[PDB]
Image (cartoon, grey):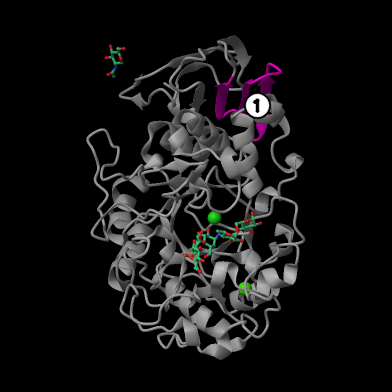
Amino acid sequence: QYSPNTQQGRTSIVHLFEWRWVDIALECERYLAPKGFGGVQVSPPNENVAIYNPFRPWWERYQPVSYKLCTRSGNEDEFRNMVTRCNNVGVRIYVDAVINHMCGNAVSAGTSSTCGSYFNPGSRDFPAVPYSGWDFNDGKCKTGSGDIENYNDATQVRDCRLTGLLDLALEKDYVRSKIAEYMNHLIDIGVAGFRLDASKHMWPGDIKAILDKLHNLNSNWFPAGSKPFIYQEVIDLGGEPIKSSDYFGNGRVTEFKYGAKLGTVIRKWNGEKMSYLKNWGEGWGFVPSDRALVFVDNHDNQRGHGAGGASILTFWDARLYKMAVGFMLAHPYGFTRVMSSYRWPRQFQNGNDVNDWVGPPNNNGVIKEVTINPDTTCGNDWVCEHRWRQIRNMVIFRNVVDGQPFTNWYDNGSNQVAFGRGNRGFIVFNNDDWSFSLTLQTGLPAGTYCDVISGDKINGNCTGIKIYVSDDGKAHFSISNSAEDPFIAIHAESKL
Ligand SMILES: C[C@H]1O[C@H](O[C@H]2[C@H](O)[C@@H](O)[C@@H](O)O[C@@H]2CO)[C@H](O)[C@@H](O)[C@@H]1N[C@H]1C=C(CO)[C@@H](O[C@H]2O[C@H](CO)[C@@H](O[C@H]3O[C@H](CO)[C@@H](O)[C@H](O)[C@H]3O)[C@H](O)[C@H]2O)[C@H](O)[C@H]1O
Ligand SMILES: *[C@@H]1O[C@H](CO)[C@@H](O)[C@H](O)[C@H]1NC(C)=O
Ligand SMILES: [Ca+2]
Ligand SMILES: [Cl-]
């Protein structure tokens, strides 16, 4: 469960948040595959409640009605077409599996779902699965509200309702089997792994029982004996009885301390400095690298949901965000996930965004197609951070230096740092309020290298900054604090 099952040489996955299947399918062929991306995390592919108040929020997708592959992203035929086309070009698909619960207990009964399936939350009736009252934790939860009231009680966190979401009785073989039937359908279609949504709200033993029922990956694309890649969403910032370590036996875990701390350092809050990043990783109290799924921001915290707070860096903070993402994919710690978002009318009032619910770009509820501009950026309000030169090039940087040790660290005691990855890559950062101009040891072979942040290597030439490395591995770096991107990165493949 710990291996990504990505094609050899590809080291990152991208979250194409709310993208339609047909859009992901062609993105796999026209961009992801040739640019060296390892895989894609897709939004929940199962039928969900259609919420009209507020109008079709992104979060309606986290309220299951059935396990039919029928959503605003497309139907089953379109899903399978996507998985097939992506796998054919070496790009894997990872499903966001919402298995801890069904929809909100307060949702009106009827057929207000993405595929017309009937459901009755009040009576716990979900005939499309089918689930009944005997399949929920109503009689198991011990809180007065029936919802999770205190995270200091590990039992209610698992047996009660997360914000009113009907909690599935995961100890029952029937329920474990229905979830496995769903996941096995996806595995046989060709999916490579899953993001286990709300894993903190499930007992590690129940998750394990479910995973024991899973099929080995489809033998038409994967080697025999391949296991689905499993990463569990467990928000562990340290002050609770539940630890992410409790889930290591099932697969990898999301390390939310990563983006939270990276944001604080980059923003220079509480007197933190980039120079402190010398021992970044386990030294900061993070989970072991081989059990970590890292990222700067996710679909939740980029908009005030989940955990991380105001420190979280997002596309809205473009300049600093690129540096954060840059540092992340240059550093050897964990398996990296890049975020790809859509723009929404963010409206702050008293410090909170009142439009944090806004769903993906749409026309009367129908998700807009992802259009590509001549400069390779996206239209229709899709941000496409994965297409930004600075991010895309760093995704490649990670592929190029994979396996190389962390070496040749430099710091000025403040916010100007640098380090290399073996003899295959080097990166320099300037986050201070003054210019950086110094000759550093890179560990790279002598020659002329193209800075992949300010430009690209094209037709035997660089379109941006050029770095000259001497026989002894030294090279001069000059970064003004006024630069568009205050960081430079060079690697074995950007060499002239
Ligand atoms: C959001 C975060 O809360 C905890 O995270 C806790 C954390 O564990 C704790 O330590 C501390 O930091 O507070 C955090 C926030 O409560 C969990 O532990 C963590 O697993 C979870 N994150 C995952 C799962 C949920 C549920 O499927 C999804 O919710 C997402 O979908 C839900 C269903 O539509 C949304 O509720 C929505 O529907 C409910 C129906 O009853 C309404 O009551 C609610 O007001 C409405 O917002 C929710 O706002 C949204 O974020 C989310 O997108 C996904 O990423
Ligand atoms: C490389 O760039 C220079 C200009 O900087 C140009 O003279 C040369 O023709 C370019 N080389 C190729 C192969 O295009
Ligand atoms: Ca639960
Ligand atoms: Cl996540």
Q: Where does the N terminus fall, quadrant-wise?
A: bottom right
Residue for point 30% across, 44% down: 381
The residue that appears at 53% across and 16% down in the rendered structure is: 446
- The residue beneath circle 1 is 274
Classify the position of the C terminus by image quarter.
Answer: top left
- Which residue is depicted at the point 35% across and 58% down? 86
Residue 215 is covered by the magenta coloring: no
Q: Position of residue 373 (x, y in %)?
A: 23, 38
Q: Is residue 425 shown in magenta? A: yes
Q: Is residue 381 above or below residue 93?
A: above
Quadrant observed for ligand 1 in the rendered image: bottom right
Q: Which residues are magenta?
A: 404-431
| Location of residue 146 by image quarter | bottom right
Q: Nearer the viewer, residue 213 or 404?
A: 213
Asked whether, in this view, residue 173 is left or right of residue 116, the answer is right
Report x, y in % for residue 338.
Answer: 48, 45
Q: Count neighbours of disc 1 (C-alpha within 10 A) and say few if under 14, some if 14 to 19, many if 20 or more.
A: many
- Hey, what amino acid is under mark 1? Met
Q: Is residue 434 left or right of residue 77?
A: right
Magenta portion: prevailing SS class: strand
Q: Is residue 340 visible?
A: yes
Task: Say left or right for 411 vs 28.
Answer: right
